[PDB]
Image (cartoon, rainbow over all chains, first blue to last red):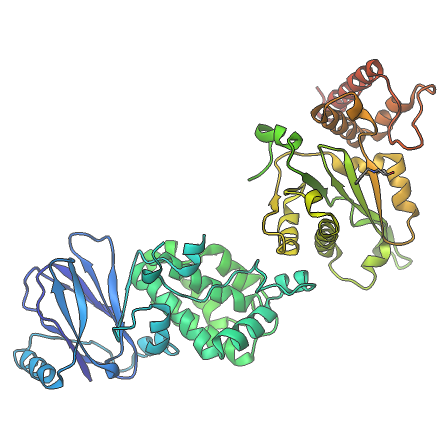
Length: 300
Length: 237
Ligand SMILES: Nc1cccc(CN2CCC(O)CC2)c1
């Protein structure tokens, strides 16, 4: 079990770790989060009590270093940093635990939610979507735009998701215009899976990461990307059987975890109704269709 | 954006543009079978591709053989249209290629966009106008070349005959759309109007009769009256 200590909490802030969150008051004696499960990426995220504008946060993996949080009063935010002196870090953590100034990552033992949301998400792949190579952790916020968004303006602060565009030469083979537009299997299997992602696990990891940034930061281009990656599979007549089964599990847990009051903005009516009821794969997402109908029948 | 009443004069500026109408591409008669089921028999069709500034009509005849063994023909018909329009553009010299293609039905937008991906600078536009180009098969010489075709064929016509020697393109297009609206609302009456006088002939190289300027004003009045009436007989007013 790993720990992310906090130097202090000088401003009132709601702190999230994965799907958990807690309120910390201005100058409350808060010194971090302990008992964080090893083996998964994690995200620690912030919403200041004053300016609910800009949710922001950090993706990290505790196996890749010792990370802590420190408020910067010049830039006005909680920053993640790496401590390279390992003895300095154990001593800090051990003192803060001894004084019991840390919250415990509150996982229920039966609960596989976080694993299920991050099954294919790898820190190495996150760092290619979020380019900041001097850090082992990745900053994301509500306002960052995607590469595809910038094509339709700061490149260093962009989310470099894989561009998917159904009316593009990459998607459409010359002389197969109608075939490839109505059945996207070529684009999914050859262009994207074989060509770009190499395997379905990297595809799913990007899809899961886009969902999580949409959910935790309200990042709009991330939501567009998550829906595009669903629609590309659902609009392919020929999908490996293992991918469809895993997609049904992936989406099931995403829909299960979404806050009910945010379904109005995070869920695209056209994609979901097309995917569940019109597409080639309309009959292949049994778990997802059942939870969607019982939880968001209005959308449909 | 879409073409509508408000930006109507853009059709007659000097940027090359084409209207594409696909309403006569896939044409069928519905009939009963010996077992008393219903079946379709396709007949020859056409793509109606028109330069509204010049009167140039690229009439691509769609022979029934193109449907043989195919499924979902109404859907294929929009993609076949887009393939043939794209092939036409590619066949034209660069300085004759359109800068915009306006489709008369919105379901053509995606098929044409996908077929024209090689031409990113050609704008594909819908229209809010309810243009009467479906009535082109009520023009006798156009209907005649479609029905006689034994193979795929492109046939070229000026749909304005020689009108542009005497009138502007705006006025020529208004005349054309009036004639075609009349033919669509009441074909028999419209054709009676155009031919009632035997002394006015259609030149061998023309589609419409050789009316004088005065006779066109009378003709145009008669077609207006028809369209109001048939709107009477239809809405009882
Ligand atoms: N659609 C189209 C394209 C180019 C030119 C013309 C004019 N053309 C039609 C009649 C032929 O006897 C020769 C003249 C029409």
